[PDB]
Each structure stands twice: as structure tokens, then as C-alpha cells.
């Protein structure tokens, strides 16, 4: 009774339903199959129907609503619904009563119109295909950015909006109010705030929005944390608003509304320009849909108050797992057509569930769609594009793992050579503190070997010991040996309320300087770094609380929802407080603070031999400069003793050494190097006049 072609179309649709593992074979499956059927195809072509858009809409609906049934034990196969059987039976009855030999796809197409409450019939009417059309065929033959969203909808620049009926209903209801007419979509990034504004414009086009909003057109404004860079925000915006307020039912969508208003301007329009237009202050009234995040609504919008009261807040919550699975299932056919691949039902669910578990700084549905797009694209890298089959979760897992992070590079070469030699390298610049450097390098190597927490700084150290023994020098050299930036902050400048009777008397907040800008700005600008905090004992308790968060979470929150990632930072805090005796450090710093440290790196006093090594180091540096000028510097043992004695103090450590070397070894050579015996090279002998306790200087030209 049915055509060969019809029966083939049925088999191909039956085939697709058992590989997608659909439990039901529906009327929408039938219409979809009819798109491959020659007679039904030609009928739809005669009515000028874009078969691809119909293909996409049917497939999307089928995937969102058809239950999948792959599991274990006693279960069932693919089964035609009562309605499906009803349609085919209606076609057979019509055809037999009409005097025709066989049922064709076009006859089934006529039968589908009688399924009044079906999605298939709904889509046919949406595409303006009338039942009569098939019967007649069977028998015979603002200026630039992303503006007019209504126009974008008429073509296909806007991706379809799945679900979120309640949110759309609430936005429409808000726009319909006499006062407080402006919806303010509030939600996290990636949740779908822009998608809802855009999805509304589509509803206006479809006429799925009541008569009062029929003439409405949604215009999106050219936005994208504070705007004021050349032109004239005052007149251009005024001319824009007058062109919108030009007697029309125009809705102005302003994405990221927290940009223009709430923060801080520099001009004289922004907040004040829009404020006039909302109620009435001209000869019209406009409506605005805003979009912002939860934190930007509470703070800069509601408290600083730009226009907060004129807006109606609509909470746009992150979709659930199942709601997101429905969203991906509804977009899936467009991704499959683009990537030439098929995503399994299990991969789709895995994309959503694994993104929820491991991509924690982002939100659904955005992060799940990115994973799906990325997995489809990844398939192109493998030869041509390996279709996939009854497994695909493993692909999703690789993609999610790449997004959740993996930045390696610590194996057989380059980094290995520096880490293995760090101890020795630092021991060449800093003496008398082998243990300190050893413990420091053991901790860097441990973290570089992938052993440690991901949500914590590379290392958190408290460098304790006496003044001028190598604490600052070690961290400065550590940063140069690692090849990373050195971010330095003095905690004596962050005590909050101690320095004022002198002249520097501007301490408002201080913690405000670390937060509101400095500390975070420096860490965002230099993710890989050594963060040195001098004299940590003088810091204000608010700084310590901030430091506890850094050591616990590896992140800071400041400068308007900014994230300072401390994951690749070596935190070093130096203290003089105890004076290495170790029990004194326990009293000064709380157990809570001390137990979050990876190590309290102890630094000892300098020996007489270490002080002599510091002197030699200063002398070699000078010899390097002098040797390049053909000048040989020799400093006698007694003179080295003299420099050691003068450049070291128990209370200052080796702090006075630089000055002492400069005054007694560098300055006395200046005249001879410029206009004396050393002009063309030569020798300098520095000795000690014993019973005078003063250095001796001998010169000889490169004229022996
Ligand atoms: N309900 C939805 N249906 C289809 N796609 C959605 C839906 N919600 C969000 N998206 C998509 O997820 C991504 C993030 O949505 P978007 O509107 O940009 O989030 P937001 O504006 O809140 O930051 C976009 O690709 C958007 O198309
Ligand atoms: N351990 C040492 N090895 C080599 N030079 C040192 C050593 N200790 C001090 N110095 C010299 O003295 C100066 C002061 O050292 P520094 O690390 O800044 O002291 P502190 O331990 O108070 O932080 C350094 O710049 C360095 O020139
Ligand atoms: Mg957006
Ligand atoms: Mg200081
Ligand atoms: Mg110090």
C-alpha cells in the first residue's frame, strides 16, 4: 500500500532511531524522514520551503523531547507512537478512498496537517505551508556593531533560545508595566543574559509576543568597565536617544550596562544622559533592557545608584544539568552539521556534567557548549573527521581536561638543569645559608614536579633571621634564576595608622591600595612571579587575612570582580621580628598563619668566613669590570680583613658592605682611571697601613 520510496524513507528513519537509540518514533521523526523522500521534498520545494531550516528545527525538537533508552536488563526497542501510526493510517485511508494505487510521502505530508497538536504541523504552519498547497501540488503540479536584533532574527545571525520561558515571560511582563518598565537581567557570565534579549527579538518577529509589543524593535547598543576615549559621549548619545525617542515603541538593549553607569566616568553624559529619558523629560519615553552580573548589580548599581530604582531585576540563574542537556540537544544538530560528526547522548551529558565538576570558574550553558564545539573541532585534526559512534565520552574528557588546565614543561631538558643546580647557583651569590637555600629549592622542585595543590601558590615562605644576612638577596636571586618577575611590597608602608607626625601623612585605607589596585594589578600583570613582602611583622591584620586567602585559595578578589591568580607565584615574606629563639617567631605570628606556610625558612648569622666570602664576591665584581679595561686589582689579606670588619655589624649584618666597597675600593680609582696611570690599563694594589688602620693604594701603568 506504501511506495518503495516511502518505505525506504521509513526504514532510514527507523535506522536513525536505533543508532540514536530513541525509544519512540514520532510524527516529527516522520516529517524529518519525509525531507529525504522525493515526493514530499518536491511538494515542500514547490511551497518555497528552506528544507535545511526545517531539517534543523525538527532534529532539535526530536533530540530535546525523545527519551533515549540505553541501559541493561529487560527493556524495549524503538516503537512508533500511536500518533505516528495514526498519520500513516490516515494517509492510507485517504489514498484508498481517492482512487490511488500507493501512498507517497506527499500524501503523508497531507495527513500530518491533521495532527492538530503536533510540533510537526506547527512547524509546517510556521514555514507557511498550508494543507491546500500540498493538495494542489499532488493533484496538479543607530550605526554599526550588532544593532537591529529584530532584523538579525529575520535572517539567522542569532542562535535559537531553548527554554527559559519563565524568564522571557517576566521580561515581557516588566516591559508591559506603566512604571519601572526596564528589565535588568542579572546573572553570572555565560548563563545566557544576551541570549534572552536576543531570544526576545525573535519572539517579536514570530508574533509570539502580544499585540502591544508587536511593533517593538530591539536595538542593541555599541558597548563592551568604563568608557571615555575620544569623540564626545555626551552629544552622540543624546542624538542616539532622540532618534530612539522619535515617537516609536523602541526598546534599547544595553549589554553590560555596568560599563556606562555605576563605576566611574570622566565626561558629562553617561548616567545623567539616560536618567532624563526613562520617565519623561522630552516628548517621549524609551524602555531599556539591561544586563549585568550579581556583584555589579549589588555594588556599583544599587548602592552607588545610577538608575537602579527604574529597573526591574530579573534573576537569571545558571541552568541545571538537565536543562543544559536539553539546551545542547537543541543546538547539537547545528554542531553536527558544521563538524560533520555525531555526538552520542552520553557525550552530551558528559560535556555538561564534567564542565560542572571541573570547569568551576565558568557557568552553564556556555562552558558546556564550548566543550561540545571544541570536541567537534578536535575531530578534524584526526585525519579527515572520524564520525564517532557509541562512545565519545573519552573525547569530552580530553577536551575538559585541556580546558580545566594542563600547562606542563618540566621533563628531560632546560628546566631540569636549573632546578638541579639552583642550590649551587644560589650558593654562589648567597653564602652562609646552605640550609635555607636547600629547603627553598626542595620546595620549588617539589611544586615543579607536579606535586602540590593546584589551588595554592607555588610556595609560601617566611624568611626569618637577623638583619642583612641574605633574606632579601636570596629572593631577588631566586627570581632571576627562575626567570620570573619580582613583585615587591614593603609592609612598613601598609601598617595602616603609624606614620604621620613626619611629612608622609596620607594613609586612607592602605589595605585599599593593596586591594583597590596594587597587589592584584601586579599579580594579574605578572602571573609567574616571586612576590616579596618586606617586614611582614609590621603589616596590618587586614593584610594577613588577605594573605590567608592567598595561601588557601590561590586567588584574590578586587578591582571590580577581577581575579588575581596566585597559582604561579612564589610568596616570600621576610622578617626581622624573631632574630635567629625560634619560639619567639611562634609568639609573634599566630598558629593559624604559621601553619599555612610551606616553610619557615630560617637564616643564621654570618660567620667570619662568610663575611670574607661576601667581601671577595664584591671584589670579584669589581675585578670583572676592571679586567675588561685591562686593569688588574689585587687586595691584600689585611685589607680584606679591614673591609670585613668595616662592612659588617651584628645589628646591620652585611648591609654597610656595598657603601664600604664603594668608598674604599671604587672611588679611589676614579681619578687614576680617567686621568692618571690606569688610563691605558695597569695594576692596582690595595693594602693596609697597620698602625694607622687605613687602606693603602698603589698604582702602576700598563707601561710596566
Ligand atoms: N537558553 C539558551 N539556549 C541556547 N543557547 C544559549 C542559551 N542560553 C545561553 N546560550 C548560549 O550560551 C552562550 C552564553 O550565553 P550568553 O547570553 O552570551 O551569556 P551571558 O550573556 O549571560 O554572558 C552563548 O553562546 C549563548 O548563545
Ligand atoms: N648571606 C650573604 N651572602 C652574600 N651577600 C650578603 C649576604 N648577606 C648580606 N649580603 C649583602 O648585604 C646586603 C643586605 O642583604 P639583604 O638580603 O638585603 O639583608 P636582609 O637579610 O635583611 O634581607 C645584600 O644586598 C648583600 O649585598
Ligand atoms: Mg553576553
Ligand atoms: Mg620597610
Ligand atoms: Mg629582610
Image (spheres, helix red, strand yellow):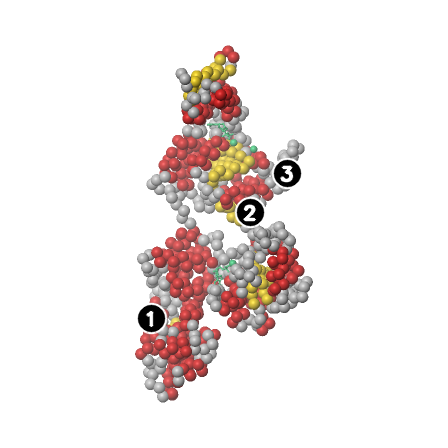
SS at mark 1 in the image = helix
Q: Position of residue 704 (x, y in %)?
A: 40, 16
SS at mark 2 in the image = strand
Residue at 48 percent across and 19 percent down: it is 676
In this orientation, which residue lies closer to the viewer: 412 or 444?
A: 412
Q: Earlier in the sequence, mark 2 or mark 3?
A: 3
Q: Earlier in the sequence, mark 1 or mark 3?
A: 1
Marks 2 and 1 in Cβ contact (< 8 Å): no
Given this view, does label 2 or label 3 mark the residue nearer the observer? 3
Residue at 38 percent across and 34 percent down: it is 421
Marks 2 and 3 in Cβ contact (< 8 Å): no
* Marks 2 and 1, how far apart at CA: 56 Å
Quadrant position of the N terminus in the picture: bottom left
Q: Position of residue 574 (x, y in %)?
A: 51, 34
* Marks 1 and 3, how far apart at CA: 77 Å
Is residue 618 visible in the rendered image? The answer is yes
Mark sitting on residue 15: 1
Q: Position of residue 320 (x, y in %)?
A: 48, 61
Residue at 44 percent across and 63 percent down: it is 328
For disc 2, the neighbor class at 10 Å (few under 14, some 14 to 19, many from 20) is: some
Residue to which mark 3 is pinned: 506
For disc 3, the neighbor class at 10 Å (few under 14, some 14 to 19, many from 20) is: few
For label 3, being within 8 Å of ligand 4 is answered: no
- 319, above or below 641, in the image: below
For label 1, being within 8 Å of ligand 1 is answered: no
Residue to which mark 2 is pinned: 558
Q: Quadrant of residue 108?
A: bottom left
In this orientation, which residue lies closer to the viewer: 689 or 87?
A: 689
Given this view, does label 1 or label 3 mark the residue nearer the observer? 3
Q: Residue furthest top?
A: 691
Amino acid at each position: 500500500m506504501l511506495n518503495q520510496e516511502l518505505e525506504l524513507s521509513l526504514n532510514m528513519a527507523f535506522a536513525r532511531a536505533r543508532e540514536h537509540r530513541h525509544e519512540f518514533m514520532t510524527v516529527e521523526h516522520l516529517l524529518l524522514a519525509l525531507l529525504s523522500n522525493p515526493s514530499a521534498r518536491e511538494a515542500l520545494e514547490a511551497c518555497s520551503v528552506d528544507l535545511v531550516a526545517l531539517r534543523q528545527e525538527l532534529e532539535a525538537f526530536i533530540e530535546q523531547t525523545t527519551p533515549v533508552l540505553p541501559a541493561s536488563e529487560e527493556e524495549r526497542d524503538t516503537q512508533p507512537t500511536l500518533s505516528f501510526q495514526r498519520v500513516l493510517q490516515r494517509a492510507v485511508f485517504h489514498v484508498q478512498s481517492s482512487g490511488r494505487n500507493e501512498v507517497t510521502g506527499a500524501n503523508v505530508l497531507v495527513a500530518i496537517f491533521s495532527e492538530q497538536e503536533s510540533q510537526a504541523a506547527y512547524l509546517l504552519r510556521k514555514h507557511e505551508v498550508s494543507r491546500l498547497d500540498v493538495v494542489n501540488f499532488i493533484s496538479h503540479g543607530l550605526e554599526n556593531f550588532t544593532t537591529n536584533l529584530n532584523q538579525l532574527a529575520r535572517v539567522g545571525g542569532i542562535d535559537p533560545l531553548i527554554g527559559r520561558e519563565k524568564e522571557l515571560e517576566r521580561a515581557i511582563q516588566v516591559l508591559c508595566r506603566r512604571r519601572k518598565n526596564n528589565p535588568l537581567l542579572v546573572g553570572e557570565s555565560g548563563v545566557g543574559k544576551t541570549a534572552i534579549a536576543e531570544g526576545l527579538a525573535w519572539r517579536i518577529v514570530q508574533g509570539d509576543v502580544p499585540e502591544v509589543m508587536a511593533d517593538c524593535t530591539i536595538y542593541s547598543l555599541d558597548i563592551g568597565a568604563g568608557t571615555k576615549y575620544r569623540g564626545d559621549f555626551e552629544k552622540r548619545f543624546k542624538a542616539l536617544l532622540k532618534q530612539l525617542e522619535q515617537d516609536t515603541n523602541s526598546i534599547l538593549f544595553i549589554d553590560e550596562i555596568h560599563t556606562i553607569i555605576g563605576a566611574g566616568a570622566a565626561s558629562g553624559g553617561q548616567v545623567d544622559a539616560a536618567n532624563l529619558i526613562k520617565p519623561l523629560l522630552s516628548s517621549g519615553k524609551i524602555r531599556v533592557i539591561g544586563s549585568t552580573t550579581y556583584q555589579e548589580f549589588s555594588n556599583i548599581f544599587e548602592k552607588d545608584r545610577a538608575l537602579a530604582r527604574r529597573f526591574q531585576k530579573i534573576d537569571i540563574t545558571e541552568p541545571s544539568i538537565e536543562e543544559t542537556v536539553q539546551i545542547i540537544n537543541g543546538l547539537k544538530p547545528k554542531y553536527e552539521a558544521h563538524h560533520d560528526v555525531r555526538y552520542t547522548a552520553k557525550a552530551v551529558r558528559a560535556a555538561v556534567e564534567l564542565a560542572v565538576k571541573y570547569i568551576n570558574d565558568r557557568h552553564l550553558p556556555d562552558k558546556a557548549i564550548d566543550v561540545i564545539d571544541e570536541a567537534g573541532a578536535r575531530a578534524r585534526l584526526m585525519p579527515v573527521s572520524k564520525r564517532k559512534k557509541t562512545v565519545n565520552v573519552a573525547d569530552i574528557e580530553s577536551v575538559v581536561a585541556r580546558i580545566a588546565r594542563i600547562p606542563e614543561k618540566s621533563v628531560s631538558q632546560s628546566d631540569r638543569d636549573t632546578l638541579k643546580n639552583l642550590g649551587d647557583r644560589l650558593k654562589m651569590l648567597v653564602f652562609g645559608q646552605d640550609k635555607a637555600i636547600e629547603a627553598l629549592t626542595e620546595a620549588i622542585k617539589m611544586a615543579r614536579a607536579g606535586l602540590g595543590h593546584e589551588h595554592k601558590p607555588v610556595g609560601s615562605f617566611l624568611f626569618a633571621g637577623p638583619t642583612g644576612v641574605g633574606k632579601t638577596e636570596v629572593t631577588v636571586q631566586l627570581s632571576k634564576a627562575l626567570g620570573i618577575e619580582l613583585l615587591r611590597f614593603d609592609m612598613s608602608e601598609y601598617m595602616e595608622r603609624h606614620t604621620v607626625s613626619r611629612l608622609i601623612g596620607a594613609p586612607p585605607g592602605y589595605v585599599g591600595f593593596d586591594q583597590g589596585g596594587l597587589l592584584t594589578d601586579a599579580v594579574i600583570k605578572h602571573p609567574h612571579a616571586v612576590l616579596l613582602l618586606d617586614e611582614i611583622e609590621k603589616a596590618h591584620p587586614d593584610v594577613f587575612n588577605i594573605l590567608l586567602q592567598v595561601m588557601d585559595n590561590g586567588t584574590l578578589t578586587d578591582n571590580n570582580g577581577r581575579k588575581a591568580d596566585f597559582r604561579n607565584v612564589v610568596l616570600v615574606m621576610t622578617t626581622n621580628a624573631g632574630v635567629r629563639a625560634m619560639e619567639e617567631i611562634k609568639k609573634i605570628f599566630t598558629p593559624e598563619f604559621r601553619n599555612r606556610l610551606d616553610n619557615i625558612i630560617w637564616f643564621d648569622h654570618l660567620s667570619t668566613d662568610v663575611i670574607h666570602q661576601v667581601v671577595d664576591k664584591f671584589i670579584v665584581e669589581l675585578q670583572v669590570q676592571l679586567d675588561q679595561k685591562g686593569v688588574s686589582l689585587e687586595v691584600s689579606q689585611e685589607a680584606r680583613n679591614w673591609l670585613a670588619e668595616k662592612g659588617y655589624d651584628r645589628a646591620m649584618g652585611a648591609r654597610p658592605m656595598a657603601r664600604v666597597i664603594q668608598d674604599n675600593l671604587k672611588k679611589p680609582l676614579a681619578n687614576e682611571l680617567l686621568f692618571g696611570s690606569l688610563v691605558d690599563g695597569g695594576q692596582v694594589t690595595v693594602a693596609l697601613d697597620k698602625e694607622k688602620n687605613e687602606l693603602t693604594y698603589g698604582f702602576q701603568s700598563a707601561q710596566k
